[PDB]
Amino acid sequence: VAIVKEGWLHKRGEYIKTWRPRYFLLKNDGTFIGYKERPAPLNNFSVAQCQLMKTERPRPNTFIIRCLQWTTVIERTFHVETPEEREEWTTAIQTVADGRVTMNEFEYLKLLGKGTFGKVILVKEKATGRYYAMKILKKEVIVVLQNSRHPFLTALKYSFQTHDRLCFVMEYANGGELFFHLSRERVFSEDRARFYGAEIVSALDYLHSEKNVVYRDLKLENLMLDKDGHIKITDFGLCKEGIKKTFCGTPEYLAPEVLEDNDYGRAVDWWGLGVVMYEMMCGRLPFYNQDHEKLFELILMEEIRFPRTLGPEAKSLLSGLLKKDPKQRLGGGSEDAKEIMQHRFFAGIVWQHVYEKKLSPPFKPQVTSETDTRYF
Ligand SMILES: CC(=O)Nc1cccc(-c2ccc3nc(-c4cccnc4N)n(-c4ccc(CNC(=O)c5cccc(F)c5)cc4)c3n2)c1
Image (cartoon, rainbow, N blue to C red; front, top):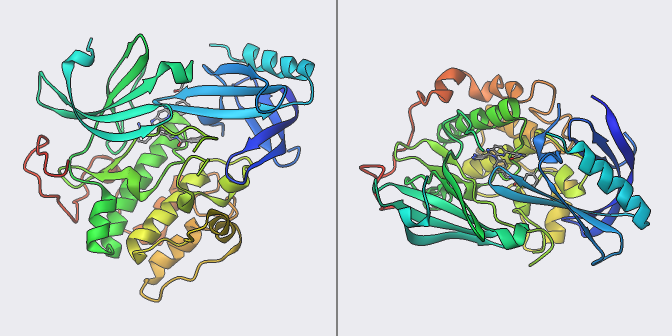
């Protein structure tokens, strides 16, 4: 509804290293967005439940908004000209911010991932023989939940805490990583890609619509398969911005407007969907270079050359999803996912059926039960 504070702030630029001035609006809902020039909400940019910290390194009058978002630590770093300015922002942000099991229950089998904020471990629950992923966050580094009712997101089974740790026991699919399946197969057929794309769209529609959340981390590495061959979108983020690549995320998948470090929204997920589906259908990334600066330039400046092997529906969809201007991009309007759901490439798809897992997988991984360790 209402703006509580507005004005310029220096924001640490994540991908193209800079302190760029952004015009920010703090709002009564918790929203805190920074536009390049003086200008539906997203919980990703909210300050609700966040931790505010004053520091003088690297620059004087710096502050940090650190948030635990679901199971992931998200940080943004800001700088102002004087200490009185800081206290004005920090007090305004602070005031607007207005609202079973233990380690012993599990066996620890394999390291799945590691970052500055913690670890993800392949785990087996002793009492049931079931396999999960435990995401273990370090309390020293950071200084009441209800799952999404959608089948292709990563559901949380348990949440608990030790004196120095936060532990999230979450689903872990045993049908293999899609990066592995695609590496072997070289390329997916358009119908194979249609099936995965439809399952991705359905999950992200849910996040965007029911949760007011952007994923922002769509990539082949974050997609795994069910025992049944259905999609699982992964929740293993551990990365901390600013320390050794010094940025978080896989740049090959990042939208131009994320790179520019302007405001962005739901359409960043559709750009991600475009890269992912392009990769499944062409067997290669749409933008690639060894050197990150050159890769960034390509994402921002270069138009794509689409292979001649691609049917006209696929090419239309991919060209739509990979438009640089987010307001022009497929799914970038007020309709969001609906724009993509009624694109011609998905002709015939019954979206309630996708949501209900009624779409038949083109590929079943070689696994007899949810307890099959073959892919681990
Ligand atoms: C108090 C609180 O938790 N707030 C909050 C703020 C923003 C998002 C969320 C939230 C809620 C439910 C969620 N479910 C998923 C999810 C997504 C995919 C698969 N399984 C899942 N369970 N998310 C979720 C998980 C990971 C991410 C990854 N985040 C980023 O990579 C990211 C990085 C920089 C900026 C940014 F906005 C996002 C985003 C959302 C969720 N995020 C919660």
